[PDB]
Structures are given as C-alpha cells and as structure tokens.
Amino acid sequence: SKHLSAYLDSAVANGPELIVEDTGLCTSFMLLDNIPSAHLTKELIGFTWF
Amino acid sequence: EELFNALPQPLQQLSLALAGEIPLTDHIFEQAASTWHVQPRSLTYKLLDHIPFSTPVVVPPSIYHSLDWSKCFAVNQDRVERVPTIDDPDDVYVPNSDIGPLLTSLHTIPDYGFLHPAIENDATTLRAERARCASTFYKIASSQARQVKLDPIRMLGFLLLVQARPRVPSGLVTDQPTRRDPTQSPALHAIWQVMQYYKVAGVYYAPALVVPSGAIWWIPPPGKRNVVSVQYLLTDLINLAILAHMTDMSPTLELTGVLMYLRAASSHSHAYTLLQMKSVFPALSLRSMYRNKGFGGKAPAIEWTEPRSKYKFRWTGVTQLHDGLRPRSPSMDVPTLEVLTKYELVDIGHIIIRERNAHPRHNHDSVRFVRDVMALTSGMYLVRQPTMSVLREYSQVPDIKDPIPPSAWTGPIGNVRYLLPSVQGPARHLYDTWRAAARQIAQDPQWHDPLNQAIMRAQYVTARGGSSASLKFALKVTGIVLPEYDDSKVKKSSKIYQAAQIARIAFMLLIAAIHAEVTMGIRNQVQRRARSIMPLNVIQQAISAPHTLVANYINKHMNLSTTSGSVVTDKVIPLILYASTPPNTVVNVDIKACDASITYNYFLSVICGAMHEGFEVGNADAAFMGVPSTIVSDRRSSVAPYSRPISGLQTMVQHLADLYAAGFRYSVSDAFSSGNKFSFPTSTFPSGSTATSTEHTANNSTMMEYFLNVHAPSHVKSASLKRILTDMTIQRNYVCQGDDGILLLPHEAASKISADDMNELLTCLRDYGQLFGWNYDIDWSDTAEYLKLYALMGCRIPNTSRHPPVGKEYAAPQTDEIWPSLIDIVIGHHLNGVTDVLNWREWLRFSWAFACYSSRGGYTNPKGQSFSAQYPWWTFVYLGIPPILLPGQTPFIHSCYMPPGDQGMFSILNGWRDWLISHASTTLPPLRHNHPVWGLSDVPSLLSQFGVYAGYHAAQHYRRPKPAPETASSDSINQITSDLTEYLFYDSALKARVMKGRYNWERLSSSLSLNVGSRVPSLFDVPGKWVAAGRDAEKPPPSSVEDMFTSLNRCIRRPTHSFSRLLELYLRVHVTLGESIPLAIDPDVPQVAGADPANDDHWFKYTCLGDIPSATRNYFGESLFVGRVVSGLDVEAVDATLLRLKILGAPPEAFIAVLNGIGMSDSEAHQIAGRISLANAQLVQIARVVHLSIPSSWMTLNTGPYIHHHAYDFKPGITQPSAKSRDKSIWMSPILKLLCTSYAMTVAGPVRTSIVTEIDGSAAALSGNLRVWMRDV
RNA sequence: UAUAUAUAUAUAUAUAUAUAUAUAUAUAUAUAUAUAUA
RNA sequence: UAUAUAUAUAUAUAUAUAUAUAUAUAUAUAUAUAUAUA
C-alpha cells in the first residue's frame, strides 16, 4: 500500500528547498580581534583609545 | 471442571451429548427435559458458586438506592401520567423503585408475592388515585420484565451447560477450538457479585419470576428491598454474556459493556439512561474506522448495470486500497467523548479508541472487531406506559418556515381550492407532480375491470382489524341496523366481521360513518420508541383508495418505487454494498418523523387540490367503486358562480379532504394503565402498515428531486459543487422507502469531494427541509444504513444487538399462548443465529439445549385434568436443525445450511446410507422379501429403534388448537359466508365465471378420471378461508387443547415405518460429491463480518458461491404466469397445479376450467394456458411442483449458476446408464439437481460438485411413480 | 557428552508502533488584568 | 453586564524534540525442551 499510495499521488511535497533568502550581509569572512589590546591606567596613558 | 460435577446426572449426560462425546438419544433427551421442569430456578444461580472469577469488575452498592415510586406518578384530567423527575419531558419510562411494599404472599409459593387485592379493588371500584398509580406502576414494571421469549434463568442455564465442557474436535483442519474461556467473562462475574445481595441462607432468591400472566416478585425481609431495575440489569448481563460467547469477543470489550450497563443501572430510570446514550458504540466504531495513515487492504469491485432501474449489479473483481481512498468525513470521537463525560464513562471511550487503533488496515480482523463492539448495545425491548407514548409522540406539529399565503388559492370548489398558476417554489413542483399522476390515473380502463375491483375489495380484509365498536355506533346512530353473527364464533373487531356486516348496504348510505373514531395499538422496539398501529375501518380504507392509487403510480413510474415493490428484500443487499465501495460517496438521510410531519395545512391540502383537479379530465358522470357523481358548487368566479357535476373520484376527494382537515380522531384504551381510556384528535398520519409507505415514499422522492434540480443550484456557493451537483438525478442517484433514504454522489474523478463542500451541501439540505417543516436528520460517515442494514467498504455488518438472544416483544399484559408454540419460537430463534453469522459450532450447541427444554410441556383443565407430552428429538431435525453427531459418524459434519423438511432428511440419509445398511445386516435378521432401496438388511427397524419415524411424523402434527362449529351458528356461518361472498362478488360476471369453472372442473376431473377430491384453488373457497381465519383468531376452548394433546400422543405412539411417498422415492437416488467448485471471489476480501477462516463453514460457503445474487439467466422464477390474483389464494399453489397438469398432459379445457375457476375470462384463460410450457419454466419454478423449494437460509447466496451448471444429473463417465432420465429429463433433471445441491449444501466445508451416480430402480420407474403421485394429489 | 535442526524463555542491539513524563510551537476553552465599543 | 483586541496563568487537543515503559519484527548470545546423527 505504501508503494501504491506513493505512485498514485504526486502531491507528497518532498521538493528540493530552492527559495532561501538572506537580508543580512553577503559576506563569509569575519574580521576578528584575536589578541586584545591592554588597558593602561598608570603609565603610557593615552597611547590607546577605545 | 468442578462445575460439571455440580450438574445433576441427566444434565451431565446432556452436556456430554452437546459436547459431541456421545450420540444423542431420546432417553437422555427426556431425562434432561423432565428434570429442568421440576427443579427450582434458583439452583441455576447456585451453580455460579463454582467459578473462580478473575476479572476486574466491582458492583457498586449504588444500585440498591430505590427512588420512591409515589413521586413518579400522578393523575390529572383523570389520566395516570408519569411526571418525569428530571426537567426533560421525555423521562417517561419505568423509574428505579422498590416494588416491595405493594406485595402480598402467594399460597402456592409463600416466598414470592403479587399485587395486593385491596389495591386493585380500590383502583377499580373507588378509582382511588394512589391505588391507581400503584396499579399502573406495578403493571408496567411487570410488563417490562416480561419482554423475554422465556425466563432468563433458563437461558443462563443453557449457557452454563454448553460452556461446562469443551467440545470435541472434528477431523477438519479448520476446526479451531474456542479461544475464549470462562473465569474471564466480566458479565458472569458481575452477575455473581450482584446476586450476592439476594441470598439469605445460601438460597439465592431470584429478584423476579416471569409467568404467563406477567411476572411475580419476592417479598424482601425488613432489612432489604428489591429495586425493579436489578431484574432488568440481570437480563442485559445474561444476554450480553451469551452474545459475547457466541461472537467470541475479547474480555476487554465485554468489560466495557458491563461497566456500560452498571452505570446505566446505578442512576434512576434504567431504560431512559440507556436510551439517552444509545448510539455511542456504533459512533465510536462504525462511524470512524480508517481515519489514519496506514490504510490499505482489498475491497470489492462492484458495478451497477446500465438499466439502473432494474437494480442489477455485477461483481467484477477487487480494488487495492490506499490512502487516497481513506474516508473523508470527520471522525465521531469528539461528540461521543463529550457525551460520555456527562456519565463519567470516558474510560470506555479511551479503551475502545485504543483498541480500535490496532486495526489500521481493512481485513477480516477489522470488521470482526467492528461486529463485536457494535454487538455491545443493550438488546432490551424497552416499554413505557402507552398513555405517555401516545401523549408524547402525537403532541408534535411541524413548523413551516414559509407557509403558503391564503391569497395563493382560488375560490372553493365545495371543499378544495386549486393552486394559482402564479405560485412557484417546491409547492408548485409538488402540486404539478401529483396532478400529473392524477391525470394518468383518471383515464385508465385497468380499473372498472371487475377482477381488479375484486382485488381491491379483498385487499381490505384481514384476520386482524379494529375500530369495530366505532363502526357499529356510527351506523346505528344513522339508523342503519347491521346484521350480527356472534354465534359464529369470530371476533367482532376483526376487519372480516365488519366487512360482512357491510355487504348488503348501498355504499352512499355509509358516507356519514367515515368521520368516526379509530382505535390504536402499540408495538415495542429494541433500540427506539415503540411503533404505532392505527387500523382504519373498512369504509375509511375504501374511501382513501385514490390516494393510494396515485401514490402507487408515482412510485412504480418514477424511480420504480425505490425498491418498495419489496419482491425479495435481498435486492437492497448488493445496493448498499455498492454504495459503500471506496469509489462512491454515500450520504444517509431520513425524515425525522414523516408520519408526524405530513399534515393537511401544508401538504395534504396541496395533494387534495391537485388530485381533484387532476381528475377533471374524465367523464364527469362516472361512478367509481359504487360512489356516484354528484353536483357541487363552483365558486372560482366571483362574478359567475354556479354548480356542475363531478365524477365519483372527485367526490371521494371531497370527503377525503374533509376528513384530513378535520384530523384523525383516535381513542386510546391502554390496558397496562388503570381506568384511563379517552379520545383525542391529531394530524398524525395513521402509518400503521406498509399501506403508508407509498405516500411517504412518493412525497420523499418529489421533494428530493426538486431540491437537487432547482433549489440547490440556485442557492449553493461552491462552483465545484455546482459542477458536480448538476448532471445528477434521483432515478440514478437516490432511493428511499417511507422516511428512510439513500443519496449517493457521482464518482468524483479518482478523487473525493472536499468535506467543506459536503458541509455546505448538507447545511443547505437541512434548511431546505426546514422550509416546509421536515427535519432531515442527515449524516455523512461513509457507511450505508438502509432498512436497518449496515455495510462498510462493501462488507455487510450484521447488527446482532437488534436480535437479542433472550429478548422478545409482548404487547399485552398476558403472553396468551400455548406450550407447543415455543417450538416455533426456537426454530425462528435459531435461524437468526444463522442469518447473522455467529460461531456456527457453538451456536448449534446452544440451539439444541434450547430445543431440549422446549421439547416438553403440559396443560391443565380449568377445573379438571392435567395433560402432558413431549417430542422425540428427531422432530427438530425435520424442523431444520442439524444433528450434532449420529451413531457411527463424527460430530460436527453437518452445515447449518442444511435444508428443512424432506430435503434435509434425504440428504442426511444419503450420507448415512452405507453405514446403516451394513450395521443393520450385522445387528438384525434380514427382512422377508426384497426392498427397492434397501437390501435384505432391514434398516427400517433400526430407524424405528432410533425413533426416527416418531420424530418424522410428530413434526407433521399441528400445534394450535382448532375451534368447534355449531348448526345455528352455521346459519350465521352461512350468513357470514353469504355476506362475504356478496362482498366478494359485487357483480355477477365473476360469479358466473367461477361457477362455470367449478362445474366444468369437477366434471372433467371425474370423467377424465385424473382424480377426485383435488382441492384446487378457486374463488368459492376464499370466503371459507376467511371464515376459518376469523374463527382461528379467537382464544380456543379447553376441549380443543385436550384434543391436541391426545391426538399428538397417539401420533407419537402409533408404530409407523414409512416416510411420505416423495421421501421414499427420493431415497432411490445416490449422490456423490466431487472436488471443490472454482472460487467466486478472492478469499482475502471480507464480504460478511464474522464469515472468516475462524468461522470456517460460513467462510467456505460464502467464498465458494459469492453473496451477490446474480441470476443473469435464471431470474429465480419470479415470472409467475398469473401476475394479478386475489388475496387468500396462493400463487405458489396455482402454478404448481398448472405445471402438474401440463406434465400430466391434460387436455386444454382442463386448464381453461382451472383458470376460469379463479376469475380469468375465457379469452385470457386461453391466452394464459398457451403460455404454459416446460421450456420457459425455470429450474426452481418446475421443481416446486413436488414441494422442492429453496431454503430461506440460501436467499443470501448466488446459488443460481451452481444449480445450473455444477450439479451434474448425468455425467457420462460416472453415472450408471440405469439412471439415464432419457426424454423425461426435460422435467426430471431439475428435480435431481435440486436434490443434489441440497445434499451438497448439507455437509460442512467447501462447496463441491454434486453428481447423481445411481438410482437403484431405473430412472423410468422413478418417473412413472412420480407421475402417479402427481396424478394422485 | 558433542554437533545440527525446530520451538519456548531471558539478555543485548537495531527498527516500527502505542502509552506516560518534560521542553518548544500552534489552536481551543476558562480565569485575571488592560484598552475600546454598546 | 455584554462584545472585540492584547498580555499573563491554568486545562485540553495537535505537531516536533528528549527520556522512560510496553508490544511487534530482525540480528546476536545464553538457558530449557523435542527430534536426528556420532
């Protein structure tokens, strides 16, 4: 009955998922802070700015 | 099994016989029957002590909460009503009360009691209210207990006896032993627990005992009290226990039924509570089966032939099931569960649903499950006070949503008004339809034929009747002195009696009497309110003739009466099967109360006007049925009024409309209530018998047709629905009978209609019916309900609950019957268990036990002697019950389809032949001179030793006493006769015809010396038959009873050693069975639920032959030569005589005399006589000439082709040449084929080819003797 | 005693179905609060 | 007081995911019984 039901009705969906939409940014590479910058508060004040 | 040890010795022997251990014998047959009649019934309950139950059932003490009866009854307007407890006005049934306080003690049995003589006296004499209320309550409560074919305890005893020992296996490879076992049945355990309350010293006092005059009750001690509902609960439990065993259901389902009954019994009004939640089981199971994903299986492929009017169907293979074909309608779980929540029985639904989910695919198991669960509904014949019934049913009037405005009518025509042409709508459609039919009836020389006139007058007389008192009063009122014939001992209320009084009178003198009271009656039902019987008087029945005639024409000439020809009821079987197939969508409809909704203000006025106008085309001066034309005033023109003549038909309408407008005036005289007769009118149509089906079916068809073709397309919204709704017509899409109707949709192309459109369609139909006040009560569940038959996916489902094993209707306070009648009850009881497919082996065992108890009985003179008798068991074999085990054979080799009568005997002997002959030779000395069929071995003495002859002749004896004549009463007999003949022979031509025919006949029969004393059917004897029927309807005097017992005993004791001449000759034939025939259908496909490999024999018989009656060339002999006949005479006697004459080669004038003897004119007599020929006659048509008929049990099988080309009467390579029939084969071969197929159907297992192998005498000798016997009779 | 075959039972793994519990989503009903209208 | 909309809580139904239990089927191991061979 499974095969017969399968062969008789084609409205079983199972279609490939074609429509996929993105509203974000078309990029695949991320700029990454690997090593954080140090916070200076006693000496060398002003050399870095956040 | 210690229970087997508990049984007394004779019953132990009987149980062994039923189990197949030993061949049954008259000796043990009597010992068991005798001892049952002497021991107290309570011992049957005592047997229950020896069953170690292990079921999870608890009987709450809530049962013993008797509600006081005094508040459940009252009298107002001098009638005892029911005053329902709940606000629901329908709680009019027997309450739950303790009957105890109303009991005295009996002198015979001091323990049990009956009503106080003081109470009934005061209610009778003083008309005291409380006395009357108590009496009414006692009467109905007793009556409800009496609704059983016999005492339930006896049935319980039967069940224990058969279930006390497992049956011995046969040698058959399909003989599965029973899977179910005792100690697991919730019903029996429930009976045990509840009965524990009714013991004082281990005595088990029965709560009640049924008697011929009703039922008695046991006086409770001061501590206890007996509620009447308990007795009802026991009956339901016993009935369920029996049914569950026979249907072989799982204990879980039986558990649910027990809880079902217990919950109902706990609350007040046990009947009402059951009635409310009636349809729960079918809705849970039948209405919702395949609403899932894993659907599949095999289904029948049925095709409806092109001339659909003929209702011819063809089996044409099988269809694979798949998900696209699964049912579309919503399930029924939600409403049912919601209802069950009210009675806190949701567990039952959960259990049922969970169990149902185990059958996703359609097969034998699924339908078997459906059959079993649907068998759980209560099988009790509910009864209520007739006064409440009549007050509750006829108090309804239809509500019309758009009445015909008064300005829509013309001026009066004396009584009727014609309908203005400008008016449209369904009413216009109805008006035109009836008018057109009236026109066709108007000119029709079919009437005024004196023979046809005789048919109509004769149709009005039956043994029953009513309203005679009203008749005598009304005519005496108008100065008409009717005759009397009391000395002729016949009931006055019989329709025959009143008819005789009328015979002489000029008809028009009687016209004033039609406006007279009509008595009424009530017949109880199993699953609904009781039905009504409203017999009109003969005069009223005569006046309403035009209404019937037009209705008949509408039916027979539009949709061919939708099967209301009722020729064989089985034509609906293939119809519903086809209607339930996957490719088709079907909807079940039926008028809510067609009898109560047809009325004069809307319906009958339109019909009367149409008929009166429709009869205008015709001779204005033409009397009809003695009603002459008259002058009536026409007032259609306000400027030119006048008067003109109108034909008799119109005069009938004039009075008929007057009567309908006045409304029927009934008079109730219920006996169960006390001194409360009264009369009140109503618009409710009589609808007491099939004579009403014609009118309602006609109107049913008309409204449906207008809805389909006009109203629906103009009103529906879905374009797709419009597309499919069009191209649809009633003649090929709708059938009906009375209120019931079936609507089936055109095959949606490889698809199914949206449930959305269905809802739209069904909704509009409801509104359409609401317009003119018809509640259509439609439903859509992809099943077939028509005339109480159920089909699911082309498989028939026997609703066994509608045939309760223990229940039987009784409409009077007294059973009013004599002991021998019980036998016929047993026979009818057994057949239902065959029609419905039960476990054929176990059902047979139970049947014999029932027979054994019934086999014995007695009677006592009103003052004098007692009398007694009992039958040898072989009687029941002749009556149509297969034997379980013969000496020398193996048990359970005879199928239930074994034919009754001589055929069954012959088949049994034919199989039993060789063993008997050989055994007789060893045991007994040879007889003194050679025998035709036997050798010298003398088996007849052996048969007498088995008492076969005793049983064979005992079954032939009559079972109802005969009333005695008298000579002055014979002057009334002559007076009765004369008048009946006078009523029959209104004209003179018929009398001349019959007299000439009779005179010629006896002259020919004697002179030609065919024979003398031939009782040939003739009209002169029809009044004699009526008189005998009328006298028979009376309660016989005791002397007749004494004659019966004495005659029966003498017939038993008389030593005879011969069967009937026919059976003697039939034994000369030797028949053998070959291989199995080719199969009809795939064994996988189920066709009848329960006819499965488990229930092998039914499964074999159906599979081999196929169910669908498909006589493509046989027509089963329905083409009788005499289409038109008068009542009283038998067509089956007439054609038998005619064929017998034709075989005897009588001269043509013999046929002429016989035909003229039943009113046929000479010209048509010659025309009919010429048609008689051995060629065109059918196998059954010619075989019936020697009373070889088809058993009713076969009517559901396609036996035609088998009898045609599978029962070889002469196979060249097998038959001995001595058996060659030669030229007489033209009429010999059908007889042999009938004998062959009867033997083949007798044995169990698959159907095999049947072959005549030898006739001991030459076939010529057999034919010669047959011709002699044919000439003799 | 060993080997093979068949049947039954137990244990483990895989798959399907049903039931129960927990979480998420949707729908319906009930209760509470807010807003609008009558 | 009623109706409509929104939010929160509770109950019921349906779907998805996870866990537990039961039943069925398949595979592997062990035990018992029966049959055959040594």
Image (cartoon, coloured by chain):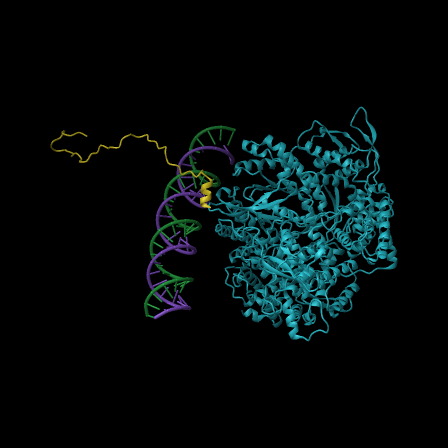
Chain colours: A yellow, B cyan, C green, D purple
Q: Which residue reaches farthest top?
A: B639
B845 w.r.t. B374: above or below: below
Q: Tell me the quarter of the picture where residue B189 sits.
A: bottom right
* Residue B134 vs residue B950, the one in the foreground: B950
- On screen, residue B919 versus residue B540, left or right, reads left
| Residue at x 76% of width, y 60% of height | B1269
Which x, y percent locates residue B730?
A: 64, 37
Q: In what quadrant of the picture does the C terminus of chain B appear? A: bottom right
Q: Which residue reaches farthest left?
A: A43
| Residue at x 73% of width, y 55% of height | B1185
Which x, y percent locates residue B410?
A: 75, 28
B539 w.r.t. B886: above or below: above
* Residue B1265 vs residue B49, the one in the foreground: B1265
- On screen, residue C36 versus residue B217, left or right, reads left
Which x, y percent locates residue B312?
A: 63, 44
Q: How many marks?
A: 0
| Residue at x 62% of width, y 32% of height | B711
Q: Tell me the quarter of the picture where residue B121 sits.
A: bottom right
Which x, y percent locates residue B957?
A: 74, 63
Q: Is residue B829 visible?
A: no
Q: In what quadrant of the picture does the N terminus of chain B appear? A: bottom right
B1038 w.r.t. B532: above or below: below
Q: Is residue B652 visible?
A: yes
* Residue B749 vs residue B647, the one in the foreground: B749
